Structures are given as structure tokens and as C-alpha cells.
Amino acid sequence: YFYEQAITTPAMAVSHIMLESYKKYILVSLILLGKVQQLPKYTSQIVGRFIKPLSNAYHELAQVYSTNNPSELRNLVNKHSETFTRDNNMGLVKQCLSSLYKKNIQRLTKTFLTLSLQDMASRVQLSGPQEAEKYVLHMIEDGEIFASINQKDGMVSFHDNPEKYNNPAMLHNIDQEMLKCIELDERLKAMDQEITVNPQF
Amino acid sequence: VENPSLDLEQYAASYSGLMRIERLQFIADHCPTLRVEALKMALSFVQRTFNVDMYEEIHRKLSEATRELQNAPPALDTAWVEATRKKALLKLEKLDTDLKNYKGNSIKESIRRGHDDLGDHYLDCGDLSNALKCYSRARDYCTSAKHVINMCLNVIKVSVYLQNWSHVLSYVSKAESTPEIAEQRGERDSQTQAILTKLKCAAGLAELAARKYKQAAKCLLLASFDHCDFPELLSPSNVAIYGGLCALATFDRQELQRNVISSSSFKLFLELEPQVRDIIFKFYESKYASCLKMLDEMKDNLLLDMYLAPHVRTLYTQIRNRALIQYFSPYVSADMHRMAAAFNTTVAALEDELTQLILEGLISARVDSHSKILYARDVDQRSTTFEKSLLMGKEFQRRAKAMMLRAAVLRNQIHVKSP
Image (cartoon, rainbow over all chains, first blue to last red; front, side, top):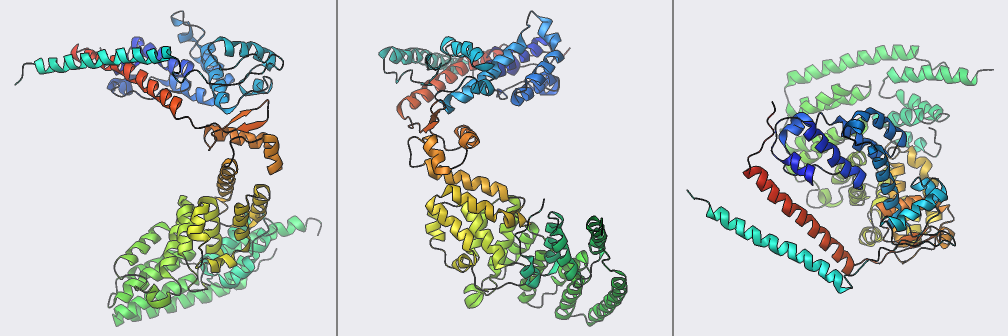
């Protein structure tokens, strides 16, 4: 959000302010997010003018992210090791690998119910079922799966059964949704007023 | 790249002109030992239409493959072919003479028909733009609407051998515009060569190129058996295979009853197409193992189509896709054990296809891969609605602050000055 706003914000120059906004933004888009974020709506011109052609870093980023190649992963890593180092921001490669396992897992999630970790060691790159044991550890660990430790077979059954908002606390989740959107519309009205408040003619 | 189940025997028996040796030499050169035979048939037909470039190309290839088989143990003769070439060029000059005679005659009728006949023998020397401009000019001899009509007709017919589709379909549209093709009675009560159907054939194989095979089999069933015959270039075997297979790869069972289970004009083609018919019957059966079995048994000549070769496996794709759409249609869970018991195919990779299908295909289903079974997901209304609801809510709220701050960046008048 921050960097999409900063970039779609009016701009004409290039900057590693903007370049690294680009950086952490698209890192979110790929490392955090499932895969490539799309072009924002009211983006700045000079980006495509200046910084988008400068954006070869994440051109190859989104490319290799599509590729699912760990070798080319580390190749691009050595490529931009400068930016890796530049602001105590090393480990971005491990971040992209995290997003890799994100892609693999989330892929397998709705597709399966429970799988062999060594087979899925091939699938997600689970590094054998035992490293996949620590991975399933992550699954039940990192807020990662509706599933538990079928340790008899180490099995991990997808559920995705959080709520029908079938607890009123979820209804109040909705309620605070409501709070936000209501005060939002209220300030929309106030500002709409204020444009009406503009000195006309 | 070799494939034996095609019959250009009957085709070069009847189906002629450019595409005769076209498919002959071409589908030959993607099928050795019938490269042998299809090039032999192209050889045999070079005695008509009198082109020698790839003729002597195949002479060369003849000597080549001869020594390749005469390794321990070729002479496609072309010197008398050379003398005959001389004679044919003589005849060409005769034709030029008659041409200019008719020019001096100065007759739309006569000069147009002269363009016609000149192009006709441009067939008989492998002469493309010659006949091309002949008929293109014969276009403009309108003493009758017959001129426009038969112009578009026979020019498209030339393109038939020529392998010319899309702006030959422009010919199609042009002819279909002014003089009301089909004469309000099926070109007056049994359009025999159903001209509009030949137009649809041009469109449908141009879409074999452009991938409109639902539309393809559409126009193909639209193509009826009025003529019962078309020995020029397009077989009823051609259009029938076209319609049946474009249907079975593109249409639904409902369009079958609509169209195929109510197929009569093509029912002539249906009896003409026994085994595509039988594969649609297996569709009715869902004998997916044996269905795709018979499919890829046909696959030999299927690839052997100069038009299906580029699309034969894509159609196999669509076939098994729609097929197993049908297959898991009835079920809330596919025992992958009992699944493959139905299929008798290793559903490891089949399954992998299926997982793609989860990604893309009709899979509203789950698999405990520890279980080795599919489990059709029930389509959620309530909580899926909740999903989308709060999803768009968070999107809207993010964008709420986003547009607030955009109103800021625009009111604050901030722009990143280049210097």
C-alpha cells in the first residue's frame, strides 16, 4: 500500500526512494503475496518514462518468480546483491524462497486433503518429509493450515472451516467492518460538502 | 514424423489440382516410407499441372532414399520432362495468343472466359499469380450477375487447391452479399454443390487455422450432402471428418441431440463417418479408456490430416477434458482407486492433469492424496459469500484510505521533480 501510493503519487524524477519503493512494494507482491501484483490505477508517468525501464531488477524478479527456479533465483540474487546489502535488507532471497514455498503449498492446499511430505517434498520442495515435518510444523504453526498433526502418519488434512460468521464475534468482525465503512461514508459526505464548500465560479 | 493410416489413393484418384500433390508431397515429407509413397503420388500427378520444381526436388530425394536403401544394393526422370516443359511453354504461348485474340475481341463474356481458361492451364504449369490475376480481372467483365457470381465461385475454387482461406472468405462474403446465394431454394431446389456450404467449408478450415472448431463443426453440419460428391478437391470424407471431430472435441451432447442426434444432412456424412460416429457413441457411453483408445487409434490419419496435424493433439486434449468433465459430473467424490478402475490408466499423471484441473478445470473437488480419492467440494453459497464480502470490504477499505491519501497527494500538489 505505502509504495503503490508513493509511486502512483505525482512524480517526475527517479530515486532509490522510488527505486526501493518499487523494491519493497514488488517484494510484497511476490515474496509476501502469491504472485505478481498488477499495475496500479493512477500510477505516475515518469515510472514508465524513467523508472519502469529502470525496473529490470523486478522484471527479472517477476520472471523468475513465474519460473519457480531456485538456481535462477540465486542467480538474480547475486545479480542484485548490491540491493541485498544496501540497507540492512539482506535475506530477500530467503524471502523469495518463502514466497516459493507459499506458491507450492497454497497450490497444493485446495487441490488436496493430505499428502506424503516426501512426495510433497518433491511438490513444495519439502526437503524430505522430515524437513517437511518442520514444514507441517509451520503449517499448523504459522497460521498456515486448517489441519493438525496426524502424527500416526504425520498427515495434514486441509479444512478451511474458520467461520460462517457462525459465532457472533465474527458478526462483530463484520460490525467493525461496519464501523470503518460507516465513518468512511460519513467523512465522504463531509468532504463532498467541502467541495460544495469550494468557492464556486 | 511418419504416419501410415491415410488414403491418398482415392484422394489423388479423385481429389486433384494443387492440394492433391500438396498433401501428397507435404504429408509425405512428414512420413518416410510414405514420404516414399505420397511423394510417388505427387510424382504421378505432376503429369498434370506441369510443375517440376519440387517435382525434381523429389527426383533428388528419390535418388537419395534409393541409395539410403541401395546402401548395399533414384532416377526420377525429368529430361523428357524437360522436353515436355518446352512443349507446354509452347502451348502457353499459344494461350497468350488466344488471350490477346480475345482481348481484341473486346468482350466481357469472351475476355472473362479467356482469363478463366488461361488460369485453367496455369494449373497445367504450376502457375499461381498468372491464373490469380486472370480470374481477378475476369471479375470485372460484368455483362451479367453470373459474372460476379461465378467469379467469386471459381476464384474461391482456385484458392481451394491454392490453400487460400481468409480473404478467400472475403470472396465468400462478397459473393454472399449481392446476388443472394442459395437462390432462396438451396440454389433453386437442391444446391447440389451447396455453394454456401463450400463457403462454410472455407470458413471452417480457415478456422481450423484460427481455432474455431465449435464454429467449424457448426458450418460442417451446416454443410449438407446435396451434391453427394465433390471430386475437385474437398472430399465428403474431408468435411465429414471435419464436422464429426470438431463436434466431438467442441460440442456438447445437448448440441448432439440438437444437431448430431438430429444430424441428417450430415447423417449422410455420419454413415460416411463410421468411426468418428462410434467415438461419439462411446461419448454417449463414456468409455473413456476405450473412447480415447479408438481416438488415438484414429490418431494416425488424424495427424495425417494436413489440417488436423497442427490441431490433432489439441482436439485430443479437448476430448478427454470434456470427457472427464462428464465423468466426475455425476459424483461428489472420485475414488481415485475406483477412478482408475474405471479408467484403467495410471492416474498419477492423469491425477496431475486433474490437479491442473483443480487449478483450471471443473474440479470442485478434493483429494486426500494420502487417501488417493477425489472428493467433490460442495459449492458454498453462504460462507463463500462471506469470503467475497469481507474480501471486497478490505479492498474497499484499503482503497478508502488510498483515495484519501491520493486526494492528499493531489491537494498537497507534490510531484517528484526530475532534477
